[PDB]
Amino acid sequence: QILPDPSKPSKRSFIEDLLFNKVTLADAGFIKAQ
Amino acid sequence: QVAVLYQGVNCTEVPVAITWRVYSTGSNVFQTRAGCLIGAEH
Ligand SMILES: *[C@@H]1O[C@H](CO)[C@@H](O)[C@H](O)[C@H]1NC(C)=O
Image (cartoon, rainbow over all chains, first blue to last red; front, side):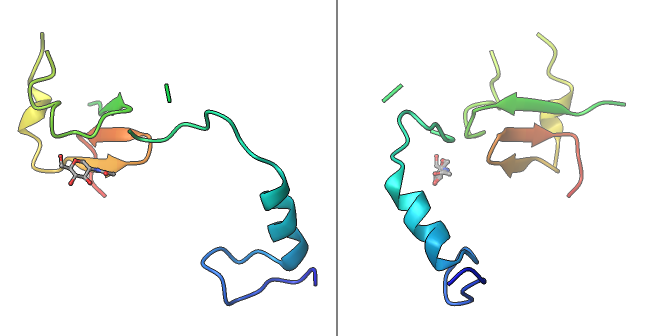
């Protein structure tokens, strides 16, 4: 549950996925509301 | 020698940037998530 999971585009573990879903970014910004 | 990064631009509109336009000749224009890089070989 903490080692990488090869079956994802980003080689993230399970708990890392949970953590990345719990936090919701605001006005992140990319190459293109701003 | 130098390279130029127009940052935050999908460089289809940069060919007409606006003084100097020596570099737009290019032939090695490259597109990165930070912008468009001109004068550097990939
Ligand atoms: C940049 O513009 C072209 C056409 O103007 C478009 O096809 C391309 O998807 C754009 N770049 C991105 C990252 O969307």
